[PDB]
Length: 83
Length: 78
Image (cartoon, rainbow over all chains, first blue to last red; front, side):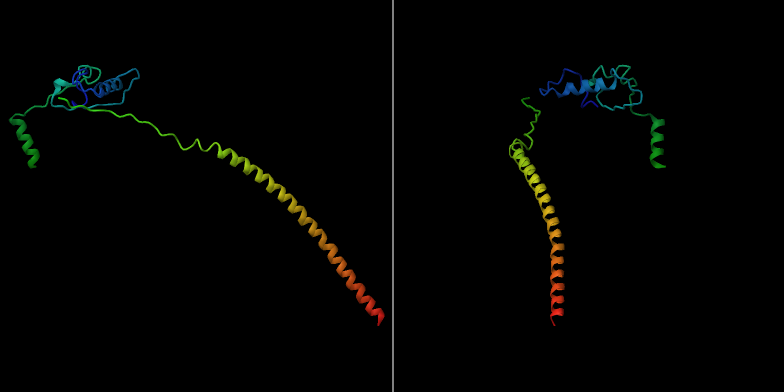
């Protein structure tokens, strides 16, 4: 997701296509007209570059970190792959 | 860092016409005149056919009358 949703103002692409997309996405996820039948999933390696207005508790409320496992997880993974 | 990028704009070439409004009107007028002439020819041809059909009966009647008269005269003569 960090390829089309960087902060608004940075990255002086002189085309002007990198702020219009962010504005459109923000206005579509949560705008004047209300939706109640959608779900959006995002995945990124650089969470510090995402726009701060896209992560507020009304747009992308759940944030999770997936990290290295411990012994009791490595055992489960090995069992899954050797069953 | 002199790496520039661009975006494109489009223009539509004029649609196929601006020669279909001077010969077109003349074509339509000529077609209308030809249609009227064809209708008139239809009427005249029907009238002519009726007149020929009328002529046929008189033709046949005169033929029959002359043949009968000739046969009768020959029969009485001998």
